[PDB]
Amino acid sequence: EAEKLLEEQRELMKQSRQEAQALIENARKLAEEQKEQIVASARAEAERVKETAKKE
């Protein structure tokens, strides 16, 4: 009985380590996308000021 626990636990650790990798990569990607939304938006804002100013 002790050994099985070890074998199931090691596999569960190994799977968890892949999940952890995935989590860190995915969470950074979300961050990266957020950094991008803020810049996409920023560019947009830069265009609006100029356009409104020309219209004026």
Image: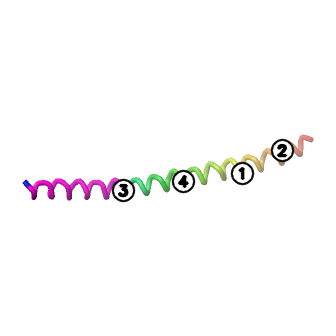
Q: Mark 4 sits on what residue?
A: 31
Q: Is residue 36 left or right of residue 13?
A: right
Q: Secondary structure at mark 4?
A: helix
Q: CA distance from mark 4 to mark 3?
A: 16 Å
Q: From mark 2 to mark 4, how far is it between C-alphas?
A: 30 Å
Q: What residue does disc 1 label?
A: 43
Q: Which mark is residue 29?
A: none
The residue carrying mark 2 is: 51
Q: Amino acid at mark 3?
A: Ala
Q: Residue at x 85, y 42 (%)?
A: 52
Rendered image quadrant of residue 17: bottom left
Q: Nearer the viewer, mark 4 or mark 1?
A: 4
Q: Secondary structure at mark 1?
A: helix
Asked whether the beta carbons under mark 1 and mark 2 sit within 8 Å of each other, the answer is no
Q: Tell which of 29 and 11 is nearer to you.
A: 11
Label 4–label 3 contact, CB within 8 A:
no
| Crowd class of label 2 (few under 14; some 14 to 19; many from 20; radius 10 Å) | few
Q: Nearer the viewer, residue 4 or 18?
A: 4
Q: Earlier in the sequence, mark 3 or mark 2?
A: 3
Judge the density around disc 1: few (<14), some (14-19), many (≥20) Cα neighbours within 10 Å: few
Task: Please indicate whether residue 19 sits to the left or right of residue 49 in the image.
Answer: left
Residue 47, how many percent across, how many down?
77, 48
Instruction: Kindly report the secondary structure that dominates the magenta region of the rendered protein.
Output: helix
Depth check, front residue: 20 or 3: 3
Q: Dot 2 lies on which element?
A: helix
Q: Quadrant of residue 9?
A: bottom left
Range of residues picked out in magenta: 2-21
